[PDB]
Image (tube, rainbow, N blue to C red; front, side, top):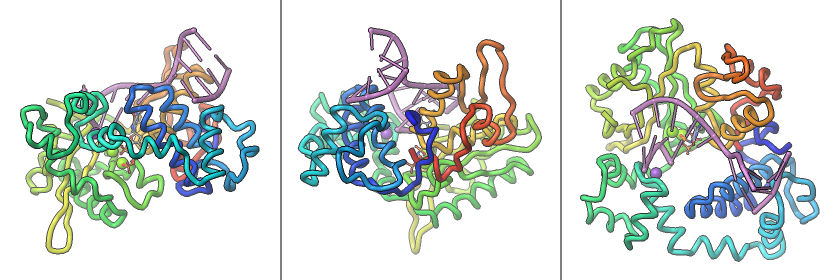
Length: 327
DNA sequence: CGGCTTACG
DNA sequence: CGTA
DNA sequence: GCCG
Ligand SMILES: Nc1nc2c(ncn2[C@H]2C[C@H](O)[C@@H](COP(=O)(O)NP(=O)(O)OP(=O)(O)O)O2)c(=O)[nH]1
Ligand SMILES: [K+]
Ligand SMILES: [Mg+2]
Ligand SMILES: [Mg+2]
């Protein structure tokens, strides 16, 4: 099928090298502002992840969605020579390496990285010498960059969840913490830990996240956070280690229980899976999907879901467990 | 050709 | 602009 | 860059 939400995509697969190469080109397209080419290369990479066996000859790409002349030539050169000249040229270019380094900083997007690049900046130390150019968020990202470049491990995640649950249970007894993001899809490591928080009584979650953050702050666990009312927090946590501690990015989201299936579906991802599912919803079904609900514009009504299963059924899609949403 | 991702901080 |  |  043409959309990633119509097929299972496991975490590990049989075309790792080919998909990695196409994702380099996708990433390079994004650094140059070409969102359309980024999407096509990401989609072609995702198709290969969904295949049941390795691609060994060009003919296997026949009829595969999102493979045209450019992506097929990339695959062809990898099959024939083990390397793609275009991909290798991107890898070693100063532009790619610096945009990759800069955009990996928490608080730095493509627009900011591109301005710094054009101004001649190239390294983290270059940015550190110009702290007048940095927001407080970027200063935090730069200071903690080395720890944040270390993958979070599944072992780390359970220790963090207990701490978050402790603060959440004091902020509002009966509130729950659900692991979402990449670790919910089965990843053994990640760039951060994502949590979704709710309470079984509609309305009780109002105003919860400031109370949660206050309690985490008082426990001494918050190295950075954005802080009147808010429902999403992007922070840097102090995580325990043997004889020391390390900084870890943690995302917290609060949703009312009525919206929990939609929020769980959205924040579980993958990011490409979510965009493809929303695109499918809008273009094939005429329904508008987000992390709050599923809207029929013609009837001006919202579909009530009690589960992610509900949502897949309402879109006419076979259910995909989180481990099969690794588009 | 137009379309390509979303709401919140 | 950033979360990304 | 590719789809419809
Ligand atoms: N609508 C929407 N959702 C998004 C977007 N980006 C991410 N999400 C949703 C879907 C994502 O699954 C979720 C969390 O995003 P991360 O924590 O940045 N990534 P993950 O946990 O997959 O991996 P790792 O942390 O190891 O890099 O947020 C976006 O641009 N749009
Ligand atoms: K960034
Ligand atoms: Mg994550
Ligand atoms: Mg996250």
